[PDB]
């Protein structure tokens, strides 16, 4: 416990399902600048401040970044006790936040805006930790590859990051279909294993 | 009241010192378990591990090939005294004449 | 004689369990030092008091 | 009405493993009958297995 | 990793990934087993009879799935282990 | 009546049932 109560007017507040994360805010016109030097984490909507677990090297200078949320919608049917009581309840439930460096600390307005996907930092709700991602650039072009034809694909619960060229992206149906095929195949085999003739059979 | 059946075709391996000898209600030779045991079936593709912690009757012997879906052991987990117990009498009859 | 579904404790029973296996029988007979034919003969032997000649 | 469900003789499927299971149970039952005869099992025991 | 170069080119592995007809258990990894107990050593309850015994279930049931699988095999649409369809093969057909 | 409601909401084949080969080597209608 820090033992001092901070002024939160000077801190960015990011809210996750189980925690609130505070990072320092240097003044700027569009509110995009971040200091990773001071950070605190708090139980949800309560005000006893505490120091986060930092699992990686953190930046020592001001960085312009963009924030995104990762999570799952929860739709529940709640009990009905009055005539017009709500039939359904929906909650966002964010679990991780990804902060990505603007390129060369450039600003949105500039014609030259892009995002540096090499530097992405993650905040995790369950572990109260901040870490840096490991990206695998499979895009030829080297370190100098253009940043106007780059796309990042995140898979695996936020644990896999890759940069690939734009045109080689998969359509939305293919991603769903690929997954269903894998699961369905494994499940049929599990069923059919019990039969005494499995060793002598062929998938077709 | 539950019957452990066999996961796949293969040889059943277990140590016999741990288990103790018995005769079943239907007349067969069997082994009774009062300690937890691990029994493995060695199918050519994979090894299957099954366990029998409660007092159980193991009906197989080491090195026996067992086919799929064959009852290898009996859990007999329930241990409840019955007030519905009823003693009944059966009569055997003779199929030939004699002394 | 012992009971049902109970560990067999009497010594005679345990030997009877072990002999339901063909190998045990042959191994045991070798220990007794008799030919295979001899085992067969002892089965047909007369129990009880054997009278004097 | 549009989908029109109906039932036919070959829609009454049976589990693939039935033959193997019935055939094995029948083998166990024959062996126990030879043995009742030869004296290795008693009658209450035959009844119960069956 | 500028060139993405992961290659499953073995026939079995490629076939399994793509979905083309293939044997369920790999031919290479099939492994031999030490001899099990002989019939004699087994207890009576588990001993196979010396002479085969008659049953009403000795012959496999006739069905639509078996007829079709055979017919397609001649054409070349499916390849099956063997010349007569097995019960697991018939089950997969009902699904697909 | 129940049969009809079930059929309407029953669904569609998802993986192996709808495509023979893995979708990797290689629905469409969009309505407003």
Image (cartoon, coloured by chain):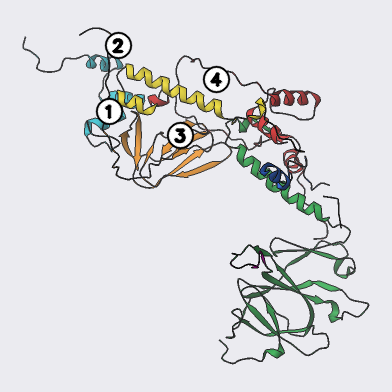
Task: Give the quarter of the image for residue E47.
Answer: top left
Count of marks placed on residues: 4
Chain under disc 2: B
Q: Is residue A82 magenta?
A: yes
**Disc 4 or disc 1, which is closer to the eye?**
4
The chain in green: A
Q: Is residue A164 above or below residue B26?
A: below
In the rendered image of the structure, the colour used to display chain C is cyan
In the rendered image of the structure, the colour used to display chain B is orange
Q: Are marks 3 and 4 in contact (CB under 8 Å)?
A: no
Q: Residue at x 82, y 61 (%)?
A: A138
Question: Do tags 4 and 1 sit on the same chain?
Answer: no
**Disc 2 or disc 4, which is closer to the eye?**
2
In the rendered image of the structure, the colour used to display chain E is red
In the displayed orientation, state which residue is furthest to the right: A111
Q: What residue is pinned by disc 4?
A: E57
Give the x, y percent position of residue D24: 48, 25
**Disc 1 or disc 2, which is closer to the eye?**
2
Q: Quadrant of the C terminus of chain C?
A: top left
Q: What residue is pinned by disc 2?
A: B95
Q: What residue is pinned by disc 3?
A: B71
Q: What residue is pinned by disc 1?
A: C16
Q: Is residue A128 left or right of residue E93?
A: left
In the rendered image of the structure, the colour used to display chain F is blue
Question: Do tags 3 and 2 sit on the same chain?
Answer: yes
Foreground pick, B31 / A137: B31
Foreground pick, A19 / A58: A19
Judged from the image, the secondary structure of the residue bearing numbered disc 2 is loop
Q: Give the magenta range.
A: A81-89
């Amino acid at each position: 416990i820090v033992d001092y109560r901070i002024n939160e007017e000077e801190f960015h507040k990011i809210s996750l399902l189980d925690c609130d994360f505070f990072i320092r805010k240097p003044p700027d016109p569009d509110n995009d600048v971040y200091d990773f030097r001071e950070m605190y984490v708090t139980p949800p909507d309560t005000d006893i401040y505490a120091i986060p677990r930092v699992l990686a090297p953190m930046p020592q200078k001001y960085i312009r970044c963009a924030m995104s949320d990762y999570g799952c919608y929860n739709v529940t049917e709640p009990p009905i006790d009055a005539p017009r009581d709500p039939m359904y309840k929906s909650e966002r439930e964010v679990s991780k936040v990804f902060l990505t460096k603007h390129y060369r600390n450039r600003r949105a307005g500039d014609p030259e805006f892009a995002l540096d996907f090499e530097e992405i930092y993650v905040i995790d709700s369950k572990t109260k930790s901040i870490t840096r991602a490991k990206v695998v650039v499979t895009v030829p072009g080297g370190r100098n590859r253009d940043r106007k034809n780059d796309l990042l694909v995140i898979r695996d619960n936020g644990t896999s990051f890759k940069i690939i060229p734009s045109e080689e992206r998969d359509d939305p149906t293919t991603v769903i279909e690929k997954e269903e095929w894998k699961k369905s195949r494994q499940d049929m085999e599990r069923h059919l294993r019990k039969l005494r003739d499995f060793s002598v059979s062929n998938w077709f | 009241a539950e019957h452990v059946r066999a996961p796949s075709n293969g040889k059943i391996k277990f140590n016999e010192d741990l288990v103790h000898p018995t005769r079943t209600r239907h007349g067969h030779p069997a082994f009774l378990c009062s300690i937890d045991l691990y029994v493995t079936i060695e199918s050519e593709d994979i090894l299957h591990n099954v366990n029998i912690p409660p007092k159980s009757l193991l009906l197989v012997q080491n090195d026996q090939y067992v086919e799929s879906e064959q009852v290898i052991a009996e859990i007999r987990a329930g241990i409840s005294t019955l007030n519905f117990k009823e003693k009944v009498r059966k009569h055997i009859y003779s199929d030939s004449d004699g002394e | 004689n012992e009971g049902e579904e109970v560990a067999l404790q009497s010594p005679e029973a345990i030997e009877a369990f072990k002999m339901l296996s063909p190998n045990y029988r042959k191994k045991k007979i070798s220990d007794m030092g008799i030919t295979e034919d001899e085992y067969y003969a002892k089965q047909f032997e007369i129990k009880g008091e054997i009278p004097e000649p | 009405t549009a989908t029109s469900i109906s039932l036919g003789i070959d829609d009454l499927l049976t589990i693939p493993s039935k033959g193997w299971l019935v055939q094995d149970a029948e083998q166990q039952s024959l062996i126990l009958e030879k043995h009742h005869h030869y004296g290795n099992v008693h009658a209450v025991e035959k009844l119960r297995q069956s | 990793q500028p060139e993405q170069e992961e290659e499953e080119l073995t026939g079995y592995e490629l076939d399994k990934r793509l979905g083309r007809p293939h044997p369920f258990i790999d031919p290479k990894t099939k492994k031999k087993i030490e001899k099990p107990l002989t019939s004699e050593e087994l207890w009576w309850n588990w001993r196979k009879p010396e002479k085969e015994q008659w049953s009403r279930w000795q012959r496999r049931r006739p069905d639509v799935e078996t007829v079709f699988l055979k017919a397609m095999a001649e054409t070349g649409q499916v390849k099956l282990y063997g010349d007569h369809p097995t019960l697991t093969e018939t089950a997969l057909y009902r699904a697909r | 009546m129940l049969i009809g409601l079930y059929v309407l909401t029953s669904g569609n084949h998802r993986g192996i049932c709808v495509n023979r080969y893995n979708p990797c080597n290689r629905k469409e209608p969009f309505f407003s």
